[PDB]
Image (cartoon, rainbow, N blue to C red; front, side, top):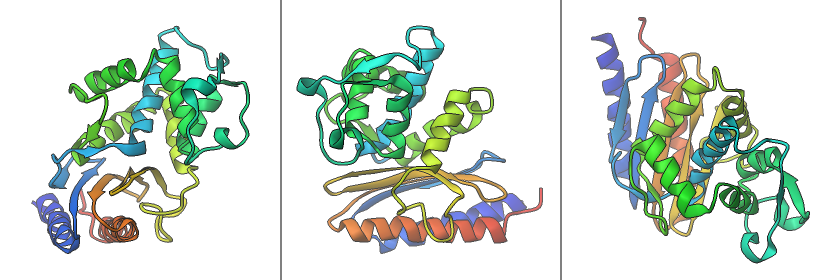
Length: 255
């Protein structure tokens, strides 16, 4: 009963919050210790933008585990297929090849677009990779041209990473790269700093973040938005994140 009281308070906060947002938003919260979730508009599908780099890296790790690739493998840069600007390290000091491990790191820590392209190449192309990650991790068929996630989808992916990193060091490495990511915004706030693993995503009107907040009783959170004002969208994510953090640290029910 005490749990339902607390989770109902989380729900009240989510409902109140989305009322304030000019645009479309989905929010999903997961209390990792109990498995209890609360969502508002948690099934609306949004263009993934860079959030897809998380399951991409998971798939790369799975592929290494299968024996088909090794972390030490040198992956060649293909100008004619891999070049992309925006976020990343590679574009701004291009090398002819990279260890697979390095790509894996850069795709998350620096949201590196070229790294992402080179990972898709390694996995047999983006259509194949997308089919595999969606089918295996979400039990869904993807749109290859315009892949989508709901906030609930994001929670399914985060839960898998969080559970399985206990026995999969390469998933722990992904998590750690999410903690070390260089974009100190959205779910990363003065309150959550040093205690958040997150993957931002941005494209035009799409502004997202998804992650795990390392409160004493930890929780997963996904906030996906589409709206006209990028600054407002990012500020909304940070605001809701801090409000949930405060509840989680101050009113968590005795079990």
